[PDB]
Amino acid sequence: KRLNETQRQNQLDEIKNSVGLTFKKKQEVEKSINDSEKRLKHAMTEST
Amino acid sequence: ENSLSTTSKSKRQVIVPVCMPKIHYSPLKTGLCYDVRMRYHAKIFTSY
Image 1: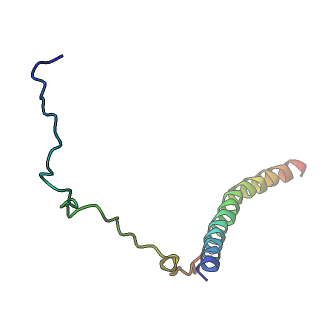
Image 2: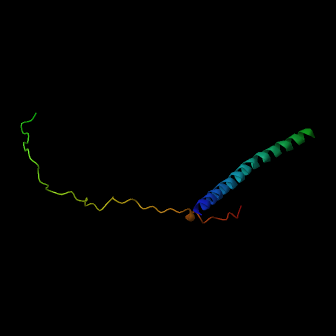
Image 3: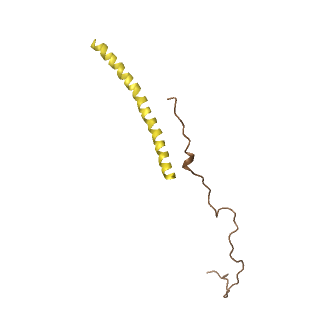
């Protein structure tokens, strides 16, 4: 029972770590996609 | 080498018999408390 318990507890730990990881990576690509959208605005003024 | 050279060609008599060493510290071990069930309590990340 403590075998299965500690497997599930390490699983829960790895889960919380992974949620941190995905929101981290997403939060960093936010500013990237923002700047990319701004250059797109510049490029559209260029087209016009 | 030395001439001090204690000459006594006989069996001796037991003087102080071997006893259990009269120490109160460290024939024992160190106590250790561990349990995966105190990794139990978790937070609910709710804000974001």
